[PDB]
Structure formats: C-alpha cells, structure tokens
Amino acid sequence: MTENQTAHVRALILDATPLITQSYTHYQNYAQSFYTTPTVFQEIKDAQARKNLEIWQSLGTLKLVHPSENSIAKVSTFAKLTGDYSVLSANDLHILALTYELEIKLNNGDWRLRKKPGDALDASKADVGSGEDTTGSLGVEASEEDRHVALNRPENQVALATGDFAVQNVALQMNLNLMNFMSGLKIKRIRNYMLRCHACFKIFPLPKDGKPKHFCASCGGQGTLLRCAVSVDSRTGNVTPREDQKEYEKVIKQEEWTRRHNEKILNNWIGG
Amino acid sequence: GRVRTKTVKRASKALIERYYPKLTLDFQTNKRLCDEIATIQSKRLRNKIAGYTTHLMKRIQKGPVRGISFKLQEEERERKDQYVPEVSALDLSRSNGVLNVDNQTSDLVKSLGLKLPLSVINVSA
Amino acid sequence: SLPATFDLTPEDAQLLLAANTHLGARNVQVHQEPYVFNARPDGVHVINVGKTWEKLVLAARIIAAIPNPEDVVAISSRTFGQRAVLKFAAHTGATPIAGRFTPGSFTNYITRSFKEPRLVIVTDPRSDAQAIKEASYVNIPVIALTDLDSPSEFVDVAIPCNNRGKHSIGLIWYLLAREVLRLRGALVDRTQPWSIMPDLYFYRFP
Amino acid sequence: KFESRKIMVPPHRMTPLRNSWTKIYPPLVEHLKLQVRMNLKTKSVELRTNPKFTTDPGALQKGADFIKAFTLGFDLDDSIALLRLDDLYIETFEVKDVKTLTGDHLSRAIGRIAGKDGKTKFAIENATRTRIVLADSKIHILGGFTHIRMARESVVSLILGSPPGKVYGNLRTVASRLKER
Amino acid sequence: SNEVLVLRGTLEGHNGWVTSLATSAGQPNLLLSASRDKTLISWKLTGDDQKFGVPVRSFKGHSHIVQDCTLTADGAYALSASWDKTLRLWDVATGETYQRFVGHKSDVMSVDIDKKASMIISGSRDKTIKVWTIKGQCLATLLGHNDWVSQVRVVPNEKADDDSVTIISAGNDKMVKAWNLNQFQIEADFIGHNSNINTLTASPDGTLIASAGKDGEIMLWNLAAKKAMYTLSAQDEVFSLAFSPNRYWLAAATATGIKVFSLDPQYLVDDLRPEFAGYSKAAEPHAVSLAWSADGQTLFAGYTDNVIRVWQVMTAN
C-alpha cells in the first residue's frame, strides 16, 4: 500500500542525465508536468535510454519545448557575466533558457530571477499574489493541503533537474530551483572545484576537456592556477571558496589534430 | 590535375577583394560583369576568370576567407573601440572600494608614502 | 632634474596595484635585483612600483626627445601586444609592427618592411628578441618592458612590469602614451586626468 | 561461472592510463564484451567475466594480455593488432643476458639499440613487422615467431656491439627473403 | 483569419533558369515561360494536387538564352527578349516568328507591350532603351542611362490614355528613369537607391512604382505625384517584383524565398520557402521570376532549379 505522493513541483526541466539515470516512475511522484528540449532528446543514443524515451512518449507526459531566443540571449548574457559560458554547452544554455521562460510564465514575471550575479532579489513583488548540500529539506512531514499550498507557491512552480555542475552554478547564479535527480529534494548549497590563481586570486571554473591550463587567463603565472573548492549558496548567490606564443597555438592545433586522427583510427578499428 | 594558372587566381583575388558585391553565384552574369569591368584579351581567359570568381562566390557565402573584404574591415575598425566597459576591473567598485592587497605591498604603500584604501590579507604557502 | 608634481599620484598607484603589476615571476636575475623589494613566501616576488613609475618617466623622456614622432617604432608579437601597440601607434603616431616582425627589416633595404628607427619599444625581449638583435646591428636604443626573468641583455631603460597579464601590459602602454602626451603638450594641465580610459588598450577575445 | 584476474599497474604508465583510459575501455567492453574494475589505490585492475557475458574463455586471457601489453610500454594500435590477430605475442629480455656491461657501456648499448632520432629502431619496426619499446634494461618486441625471430637475430647483433650498418645490411637481407616469401 | 499560400504542384520542362513568366487575360489557363534553355515553353494547366497537364509548345529561334517574355490581352502573341542582341514576336499556337527586332548592339533583358498591342519597348544592358512597333521599325533610341538597364515596364494609364504614354525603367546605376513617350525625353528621375536595381513594376492603377535590387530596399515611389513615399526592407537581394491585380499585395523574389508584403495594412503576409532535397543552406535555389494571374488568386513563381512553382490564395480560420 504505497502512499499517494503528491507532486511538489508543477513543472520540472529534465536533463539527459536525469532522463538516463531515472525512469518516468521516479519523476512521476515529484513533478506534474515534464518539459525538455528536442536537442537533448535527439542527443540520446543509449538503448535503455531509447526504451525509456519510448515509454515516456507512450505515456505522453514529456513535452518537447524549444526555448525562446530572447531568453537564450538573457541566459547567454548571464553566462558571460558569470564566466560559465565557456564550459556550458548549447544544449545546457537552451535548457537554462527554457527553465527561465518556464519560471517567467509560471510566476508571471521575473521578480524571482537575478539579472546579474550578486544582485539582490526583488522581494517587493512577492506579496502581490555529489557535492550538493541538500540539508534542510528533510524532516518535512507535509500533509496533502500543505503539499497543495507548496505547489501553489511560486518558489516550487519550476525546477531544473540536471547533473551539470556548470549548469547548477548558472542556476544558483540565476537563483533557480535545483532538484536532485535521485532524491528530488531542493538544493540549498553546492560545492564544486574551481581554478584559483595563486597570485592574482582570480576565480575560474574547471575545464570541460579536463586539460590543465598551463597559463592563467588573467594572471599569466606558470602554475598559478590551483584546484580550489568553492561553495555557492542559492539564497545569497555568492560563490564562497606563455600562451601568447604562436608555437603554443601550433601545439594546441597539433594536439587537436592528433585527437581527431586517433578518433578516426578508433572509428576505423571499431568499424573494420 | 587541372590546377588553374596564377593569372586567373590573382585576377579573381583582385576582383573579389575590390569588386565583391555585384558578383553572384551565376557564372553567366559574371561573364559580362568581367567583360564590363576587366580588359581581358581572350574569351577563354575571361571564361576562366569568370568561372573562378563564380566558384569563389560559391564558397564565400558560407563563411569568411583569409583575403581582404571591406565589409569586414569596417567591423574590425570599430572592434578596436566599441567594447569599452563603463566600469573596468581596475575601478574601485569591483572590490567595494578597498583593494585585496597582501602585507608586503601594503608595506610598499606605507614605505613609499601614499594613502590608499587597502585591505590586508594574510596568505601563506 | 624634474618638478615635484611628476611623482606617483595615488590614483595611479591604485591603478597600478589594481592591474597586479607588482606580482612577477619566480626567478630573479642578478641584473634586476634592485627592482624587487621582497618575496611573498610562496615564490612570487613583489616589485618596487615607484621604480616602475620613474623608469617609465625616463622612457617617456626618451620618446619625447626624438624630433620626428613617426621615427619611433613599437614592436609586438604577444596576443595582447598587437592591440596595445596599435592603440599606442594610433595615439602618438608611431609605426607599429604587429604579429610577425619581418627578419631583415633593420638591415636589408630591399624588403618593403625595411624601416630604420631611431628608437624602438618592445613588449618583451624574449619573444620579440629578433627585433632586439637586428636593432643591435644599426645602433638603435631600445626601451623595453622586462619581467623579472626576461633576458636583460641588449636593452637600456627597461621598464619592470608584468607582461604575463593583459591588465598590466595594456595599462603600462596606456601610461606610456599618457605620459608622453602630457610631456609633449597635447594635454596641458598636469592635474587633469586623460580623457581616454585604460580599458581601450585592453585585449578581449570574443 | 565468473572469473577475475589481478594485474599490476606500473607507476611510469598510470598517467597515460588516466590520459587514454577513455580510449582504452569501450572497444574491449563493446567488441570483446568484458567487465573492468579499477583499484587506483592498490595499483590493481579487475578483469572480470559473468555468465551474462558471452561465453568466450580465451578472450579473458587475451584481455589480461592487453593489460600485460600496456604494462610494458605498449600503445593502443598494437592493442588493435592484438585484437585482430592471434599470432602476436610479447617478450622481455635483458641487456646483461647477452654481454656483461656496466654503466656507460650499458648507456652506449641503449644508444645502439635506440640510434640517432630512433632511426635504427624505425628500421627494425618497419622491415620486420615488430614494435619496439626500450626500457632501462629491458627490450620489448611484439609479433609472430618468424617476425620476432629475425628481430632476435638483429637485436643480439646490435647489443653485442656490431655496427648498425651491418645491422641494416642483414636487416634488409632478412626482410628481402621475408617479403619474397 | 489568414490568407495562406500553399504550394500545389511543380512545372518541370526546362533546362535553364526560368527568368520570366507571363499570364494571359483572354484565357486564365495560359502560362508563358521564358527560360535559359534557349527556348520558351507555353502551358495550359490542369489544376491538380501534384501535376499539371500539357507541355504545349517550344519556341526555339534564339541563338543564346532567353530572358523575358510577355503576353497580349487576348493571349495569342508571344514577345521574347534574349541574349542574341535580337527580340522575337511569336505565335503561341504553332511557333511562327512574325518579325525579329534588330537594333541593339548588345544583349537584351526586358520587353513589354502596351495595352492596344501597338507600342513595344526593349530593355538591354547596352545603356539604350529602344522603341519598336509591331512591324519592327526602330522609331526611337532613348539614351541617358550610365549603366545597365535591367528592366523596363509600361505604366497602365488610369484615365484611358489621356495623351501621356508613360514607361518606367530601373537602371543598374542606383537610379530609376521614367519616360514620357509623346515627345521622347526624360520626365522624372528617382534617386535614392544604393545598389543595382534588378527589377521594377507598376501598380494596376499606374500610380505606384516598386523598385528593389541587391540592397533589399523595396523603395515605393508615387509616379502620379512624382515623389518618394516610403521604403520597405527585404533584407537580401531581390530579383523580380510584381503587383497583385486585385489586392494591394507586393510580392518580391528574394534570395531566401518569396516575401509577400501588404501596402494596406503595412505587414508582411507570407515568406514562401519551398522544400529542397540534397542541397545545402547556401545551395538552396532562389526565385528570379514571379507573375500574378488574371484573377489575383494564383501566384506563379520561377526558380533556378528548372522548376516553376505556383501558389494559391485561400482563406484560413
């Protein structure tokens, strides 16, 4: 006799990681509406993921929604302000733009969203109606009327289910609701590793390709970049913790050509 | 191999660096275009040059090529000055008016004899 | 032999410590030991910025000492350096060399890249070392921007700064430009700040 | 009906292990259908099988041979050749086993098997269908017996102190009646 | 409530670029096509959802490719302009050439006949617009253009030809010329274009001039007031223009598609981009000719991939 677990979120944006890791039954008890981008669905290539996508398409709960271009420009401006645009993919930017558009449509405005990083939220319009620290969401024995009141609240109108730490930091900079793909609880703080200059004290994120930066982006010190753990609070929005040679560009192009030739040789070995 | 001669290549390079916009993907218009602008002594060579300008109109419409075009060079003439920030990183408000300076450079400030909004930060190893 | 107004104005010192010019490399040569004050104990040395100010005051006096303003030549091959020297050449009328400096340009009059200067500014004397050694053949003073582990041979009036960061190189080119235009006479009042901001010289990669 | 083998990871090659492991595991996991588990702390790799895998008992020995190959300096294209073929095997041998050498004699013997820009090493991979990795005192040649046997004759010529020109002449002689047949 | 243009079929009979389309007023079924396959092909069309009926005639008399064609009010004569420095008058039933117009020293781009079938102009890139009759006598030679004359048209008179024979020509010197053909001199000049003007057309009442070219500026001139009204932006290069005979629609043949603008009210109606197979986005065929039918419901359209398309006006929800 399973209890009727009511959905605490009206709409949840699902990434490829939560779609591959969890089934539709795991997300059925948490969210009422499922929305996703078509490019993220087209990027799925695993057979069990294709079977789960076919089961979700037979269920019909997932909505394939493309984000708007103006919200994409706002998300790109926010990512350029936060510096996470270099690591974030275009699908991640489109998912963030679709989440921003869903939060604008659900809350009937952008009062809960921060235009710039570190900007204070406009709380005057609220009276007109894995390294993730998810503590504080436990021990809440809400009733059915309390679950309906929480789903009627504007803070639980939209959620972003993703596994990308750059997208999670972009949502924390945008003060967006982040939910665990396995637990479903609202994320309060996230701890990630960031590159810190040992002299200039400049903060940059981890690389997407995993290659270590031999020169810093601002300092230029050889070995000045160090792995520094950074914590980001969703309420505050504050993250709490040469290359000029043409031969360097030639070495980078030779490494890229070697990686492409190795990928071609691996594809010929697999297909041979 | 049918590698074209250097006169056709250089004439097409000059006529596409200077006479870009009226040339198009149609060879038949480009034939009397290079008739009306260029004095080429033979029908064969002007057919070579007109076909090569047609092919360079074919791949120029997909992206930029290393050669000179005007409609980009105005754009890197305002690329030099259009992105001036209203507040730079060297301004005070990005560090709330007080600098993030170690003890030794604060000793430089108090030894040289200047007054400056410094926050001493203790760093080690 | 200078008036007392020429020294460090405190907003320029705030500007210098904002661009992290005082941070440098880990090796200290025998020649550039007086530019260091002491070492922050990780391996990073901190430099006397009053020496950088008064040393660029010398370099500004060298540039103002030439009669023909088109005869000074700026040299660059670093990625920040091309933008820095094209702004300097736009603002003082110098002749810039951006990107690959052509060999045989200071001898060999045949080449169209033959310019003979009387005065040469170089972004760093290691990557642009070929203009240094070709200017060592036809008797040219070179004032340069040297780090704490730059090669110190064949330079005179060398300005200690940071060539590693774009902040420091764009700022130090901006300060040389404003020092020579305040010394030539294009901006009469010594009290008045220069109308162009230093972030014009700063490099952005889109 | 599981089976697991235990193998040792050298310290000199664990950084290319973590560099090119993304190219190492999915060809063998997809095409050869095995299971791999790491122990990065205890320098051990767990190559395991399952009845839920395909029944192929010899490819478990082959997979242990791929990681035994990668133990001793060997790249991934020789792992593709070891995937596709069966006659290709591995060998070690010592510099001191031919001739008692010491110090700079050892260094000159390593220089003789290495050569100027690795050119005598290049001449011994291309003419014999062999692949060459030099250790501090170990020589490593892959391949089949007709191939590695004339590789033996060449390398015991060369580590005995014979000049590399006689090595080139005997090398093209044995390569000539190698490709002749 | 919207008026939606839906593609209903194709017309393939050519081997060159279909550079002109002509419609008839005596019968609505006749479509005359001038193409770059050195021939002209007439058509009677059986309206179906995939095909059209009869490849009626082939008019081969031209040494080079054929640029322009026009039809009479009855629809019995075909008047062609080609690159062989001549113009030809055809019979649409069999293909006899009545007379060949030989006065031009270079290649001809446009031809237009009057309303009474007596008064023939010829537009060529030799900086010369020549005047012909039906029997083929060159009675005038109009000069003044400093560059190519891409297109010529005859303005429809609004007061039953009150002794003002007016024609309009858009030159390739960023300038539009309008002539009065009673005394053969320049009447008005329309300065304000910035690139070469590929086409121009006249309104059915004869008071509006729509000219566009490479710059994408469909500049609307008022011919009756002899002034410039306003500018419409069509982005990319525009090849052919035609006015709706019943509606106030102005449809352009752009390089990306067919953009249909509306003069009252000022809005863009449709952007017709047909589907293509096996071609890149920089390799999609574009429209170089279009023509409106006698009722204003059928929009003919000629492209560069040897296929003539049609579009019909319906009423949506």
Image (cartoon, rainbow, N blue to C red):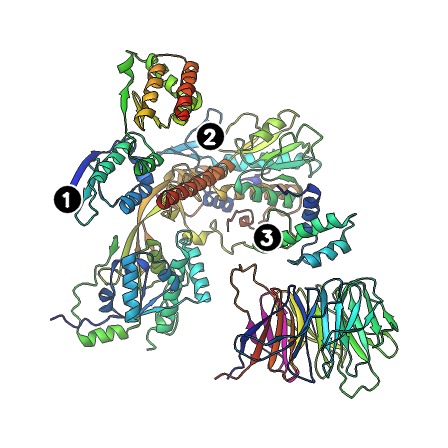
The secondary element bearing badge 3 is classed as: helix
Chain that bears disc 2: C
The secondary element bearing badge 1 is classed as: loop
Q: Is residue D99 above or below residue E238?
A: above
Between the C-alphas of marks 2 and 1, the distance is 61 Å
Left or right side of E298 for A230: left
Chain that bears disc 1: D
Looking at the picture, do discs 3 and 2 lie on one chain?
no
Quadrant of the image occupied by residue A101: bottom left
Residue B107, visible in the rendered structure: yes
Q: Is residue A36 above or below residue D171?
A: below
Residue ID for mark 2: C149
Q: Which mark is residue B59?
A: 3
Residue range of the region highlighted in magenta in the rendering: E245-272
Type of amino acid at the residue the image marks with label 3: Arg
Within-10-Å neighbours for mark 2: few <14, some 14–19, many 20+: some
Predominant SS of the magenta segment: strand
Left or right side of B69 for A2: left
The secondary element bearing badge 2 is classed as: loop
Q: Position of residue E16 (x, y in %)?
A: 65, 63
Type of amino acid at the residue the image marks with label 1: Phe
